[PDB]
Length: 129
Ligand SMILES: [Cl-]
Ligand code: NA
Image (tube, rainbow, N blue to C red):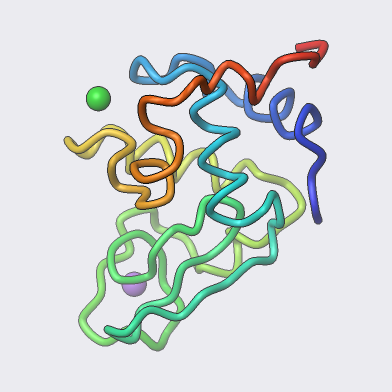
């Protein structure tokens, strides 16, 4: 499913991401935009053999099981395919674990390089949240 900007904003808010660990909703929408272009089915293979899944491009090396990333952890306790669903719940719940992991949202390269320090409020402007 390819979410609309405000549709995703509302879904993320409903799932408790607004200000989760101090990160305003605009941060989450911006990260999703640049990680997956709001597409829940996005996947990208990394050089180490791991793969990123879903709207938040969660990595199989640590957070989910895809059965093809040797010696990886499954810290979110879910098959990576769960992260591609039209229902963002699994992605959000896992993201909460990631963001609490100590490095905050810096865990998402696109957020660090494209959202961090920018006017992220712009990502929710105009939405009825
Ligand atoms: Cl933080
Ligand atoms: Na894994």
